Length: 369
Ligand SMILES: *C[C@@]1(O)CC[C@@H](OC(=O)NC(C)C)c2nnn(Cc3ccc(OC)cc3)c21
Ligand SMILES: [Cl-]
Ligand SMILES: [Co+2]
Image 1 (tube, rainbow, N blue to C red):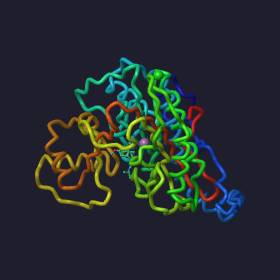
Image 2: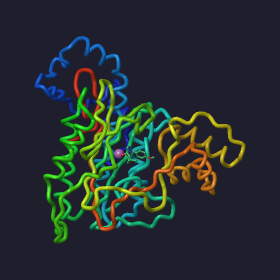
Image 3: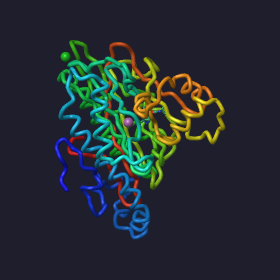
Image 4: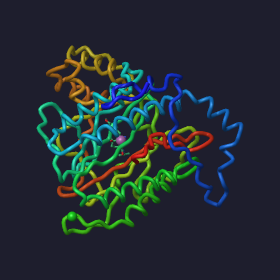
């Protein structure tokens, strides 16, 4: 009936009637000629539509409340000296409990990113990884929760040295300015341009060197679909892209990455993250270890992302060759860590937003960010 400390009560038990709290609700921006969009908020036609999707928005809100409680707990104990494995296991244990993990009905949407320094995304440790979080590290915590395949993608940056404080502010401001710009009929490239303009208004000094903060050109916000983290609409963080448009009822991950490096990421380091190709259909496999592994993936993850550690915990071993086989057949795709140049520093902030008929909801907003 109230949440414990450390948190252990499922979000579903704290809201016994099943109605989960709304995120930050916002009027859409005015149209570019100048007209207002407040009418959506009082329209019967829009209120009807919105109600027809209530159970959906409610599933996102449950997932979002789990994400707020997990991240508040992580900020309380994450410290240099902890191993990356210990941080991810402690976060994931809490997430499993709060989301009340139940197969594909509720669970973890994707592995815990905890990318360091010049690495921006897609690092989680594999077994045996001895990496320890240090005092000068800049660490992107990116973790996802879901209810019925309704995904919260939300991310923040942890530091301990105040030298990064201005970089964190830039990226936060840039992300908030993306969120503000977003709305129905807005051009995706318009959201990108707003993000860029803000991001580059920021100069930062880090150990006696000055930089203008750059958005990472090839990391992008994106639409979200059911059991589909990246559903094909992509949002730049630089100027230049398609001028296509956000539509009513869609869900977006609005993320920005800021960098003191080239502002471009390349694959580097060993792969931890994998995910079935959403568009591959059924493929009969006779090779027995490869068949078994695909069954394990279909059972436990479907089209959601997973990592090596999550196979290990299911009791699978000596599966690397079978995993490679699935990648080589195109059934599974690998997602290796994405890093800017050696020596650079990268930061991230991200929320999930719902483009409801009646209002824009930053479903994952907290008091924290
Ligand atoms: C994978 C990542 O965290 C970072 C990449 C990003 O995709 C893009 O920016 N794509 C461009 C069009 C090149 C992205 N979108 N969602 N996430 C969350 C996530 C997805 C998959 C996964 O494991 C496979 C983990 C996290 C990201
Ligand atoms: Cl400094
Ligand atoms: Co993310």
